[PDB]
Image (cartoon, coloured by chain):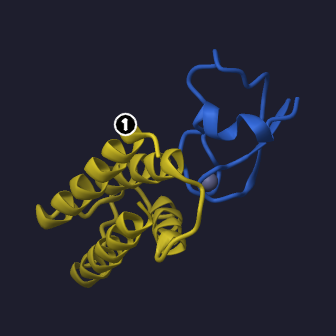
Amino acid sequence: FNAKYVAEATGNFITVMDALKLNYNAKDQLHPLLAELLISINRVTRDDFENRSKLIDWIVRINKLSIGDTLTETQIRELLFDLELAYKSFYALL
Amino acid sequence: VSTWVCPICMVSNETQGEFTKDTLPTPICINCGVPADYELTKSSINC
Ligand SMILES: [Zn+2]
């Protein structure tokens, strides 16, 4: 694997998780973070892994929100779990 | 007119004008709203 792309994807996973733990919950805060995550992941590999599709679902869902909608406290908790699981599975692929 | 497939969500998009490595800003996917990464998208581009 291209080591620079692996470092960039790994940094992006932790950055989105840290954002969620800091209470970022709006479309305009989360969309760019998830966008850059998904781009960096594809740079490493285009292969499937656990929860890859789920993270795609989330960025599609977040894109359809109106300007100033937030995720619910329990939506945030779900997305965090799904991200943690994707991160574990991406790391196993390495 | 340029057609392409989003490398994030896989939906077909259509944009006005050429889509080359020099186009800036890049077109945005209508479905997931991610700006198209040229290197990931280039094999799918037709004009
Ligand atoms: Zn898309």
Frontmost residue, B16 versus B12: B12
Residue B27 in sight: no
Q: Which residue is mark 1?
A: A4
Vertical relation: A66 (above or below) A6: below
Vertical relation: B34 (above or below) A61: above
| In this rendering, position of residue A33 left or right of residue A45 | left
To which quarter of the image does residue B2 belong? top right
Frontmost residue, B47 versus A50: A50
> Can you tell me which quadrant of the image ligand 1 is in?
bottom right
Residue A19 in sight: yes
Q: Quadrant of the C terminus of chain B?
A: top right
Q: Residue at x 38, y 40 (%)?
A: A3
| In this rendering, position of residue A54 left or right of residue A94 | right
Q: Colour of chain B?
A: blue
Q: Quadrant of the N terminus of chain B?
A: top right
Chain under numbered label 1 = A
Q: Give the chain letter for yellow.
A: A
| In this rendering, position of residue A26 left or right of residue A47 | left
Q: Secondary structure at mark 1?
A: helix
| In this rendering, position of residue B46 left or right of residue B12 | right
Count of marks overlaid on the render: 1
Frontmost residue, A52 versus A91: A91
**Other residues around mark 1 within 10 Å, as few (<14) / some (14–19) / many (≥20):** few
Q: Position of residue A72 (x, y in %)?
A: 27, 78
Vertical relation: A30 (above or below) A52: above
Question: Disc 1 marks which amino acid?
Answer: Lys
Q: Residue at x 33, y 42 (%)?
A: A8
Q: Residue at x 50, y 69 (%)?
A: A52
Q: Position of residue B25 (x, y in %)?
A: 56, 24
Q: Position of residue A17 (x, y in %)?
A: 22, 63
Q: Residue at x 71, y 21 (%)?
A: B20
